[PDB]
Amino acid sequence: GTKPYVKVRWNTDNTVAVAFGAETDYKLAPYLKTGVATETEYNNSSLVKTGTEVKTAYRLGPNAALETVVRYNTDNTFGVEVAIEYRLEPDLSVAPGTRWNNSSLLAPYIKIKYKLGPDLDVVTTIAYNTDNTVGIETKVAYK
Image (cartoon, rainbow, N blue to C red; front, side, top):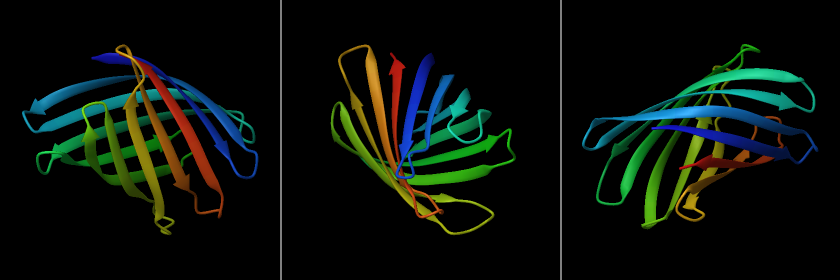
């Protein structure tokens, strides 16, 4: 249930960040999954940051699921990630989506969820931020 994970992000303006956190996921319904996570992030530009996010996956079809992520950070920055996850293979799925903020300017992104071995799942996120930069993140969790 509770998986420790580490995030590693790089942006086209050479701003990097490393995060450490845990995620506990529950199954509220047979086609509905919820998740809560908290992490500590160290950044190139803003030093330290703490973020708390809630996730949810709702089955839309046999291999499609609606994913939502709500995140708020200690620097008073928040966002909303809404994506549709398509399961391609038993250990492979893609989830193109968009990030929302009160500052508007919806930011498109894509997640690639794959399992590197039995006890490791990796989530690769490629997002296009509102500052015209591109951020590539690598999330590794211990299954």
